[PDB]
Image (cartoon, rainbow over all chains, first blue to last red; front, side, top):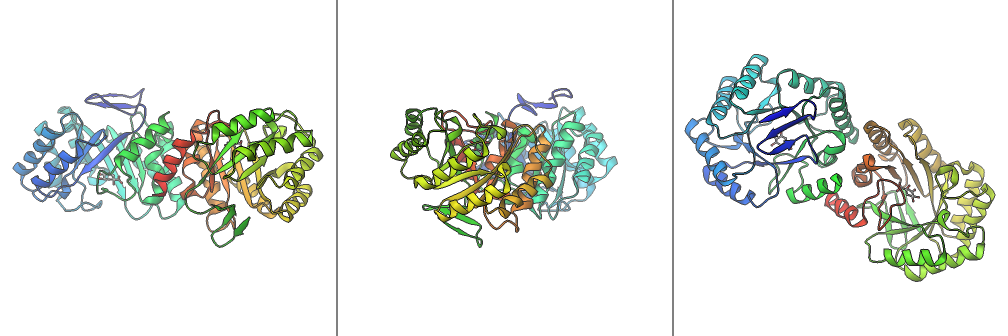
Length: 257
Length: 257
Ligand SMILES: O=C1C[C@@](O)(C(=O)O)C[C@@H](O)[C@@H]1O
Ligand SMILES: O=C1C[C@@](O)(C(=O)O)C[C@@H](O)[C@@H]1O
């Protein structure tokens, strides 16, 4: 993959994240290899840019062989889209829990497989562990989306910016933050932080969102405010506020014009 | 017309402004009677809710009979959409100048015609004459959109809110403000003022917009943030940032559903 600090872009495959209209990410959440393959097949007909595999939804996550088998199955079905490997931790709202060591080993195994283009690492996993794993990913030509989630509130704009800057400091290729609005003002706080980060500090693409139906604007206005990607739902949403993939592309295309 | 402070609505004909998805306004901008008639024909296959006649684009505005005939010509083409009579003053970006007295007489004549459902009165016309004209419009069953426009900058949110509050105080059925963003933050300023005024405070619908391409998101997000209507373009836009009416309705429907 490539990255430019001037264009503030990350290029994975031929996809240029940070240029033009925001890119669409869709999450695959199957429990079994059968569910993963059927979802992948169904998704192939959809118009998205990046496939996020939510590995925390996978029952056999603790069996190394099974994870590799599922990654391979996805790659065989969805052959022309970057594959993002994401174990969302229990701490940050994931479907199952792993020790820090297990979580880092899981991500290292994904990097080593050569089957995934990007991995998601959580900002608050631990500095030593994050830096070591970012380095390992980079040594293997795998990009890192570094993430943070607040499912119950929206921190101050200053705190949101501080977290995004810390992700940059840790070597994140793409800093990403998702927060929960409790008011309409909270949605605008997330957008304010997005504009501030993108205009003042970012030298790479960032991804931001205010969850829930109230925060939907944050999933649509990335081109003007400075969010490089957005999540859409093919069937079931991976988080509240996501709109259908078809509708999402329609809105982004309208805004790009 | 009707109006309710329960649901913060204004009902003109069967159209309920302030309920559900934002309503769409399009502007008619012809120089002569036959120009406005031809434009009205062009607009008839478009999906919009309210027809704004931009009377300041009309060459013979000082000839009362000409203005009446033009209003009549419009109503011959467009029979199923409320007609909003708007002379945008030179001071606020209009295409020609009229004295305050001429402007007030023009609006009173529009009210008397029985051909217009609504009139636009500018907040900064003069408080006393605005109050008197609002009273006259109301006595003749004509609703009033009270407006303010800043085509060059975005005032502070507190100032935007003060203006919207003053419009309520002066009797506006629908306060309306349009401002010009010079930075991305300015768009957020306009949305912030929209929420501050509208959310659990205003007792009637309001219309707000951040103009230009940078502010287009403000024309789409009214259902969440609190703007009851939005302007689109059929052929030529009447202000920078308006997108096609078809595209506008597409996004509004996506966000309502
Ligand atoms: O980080 C994100 C963001 C997300 O939470 C959203 O709100 O769209 C959806 C998750 O699957 C993904 O890992
Ligand atoms: O008040 C408005 C708003 C507007 O300026 C706009 O930005 O859509 C278009 C004008 O025709 C109308 O009178």
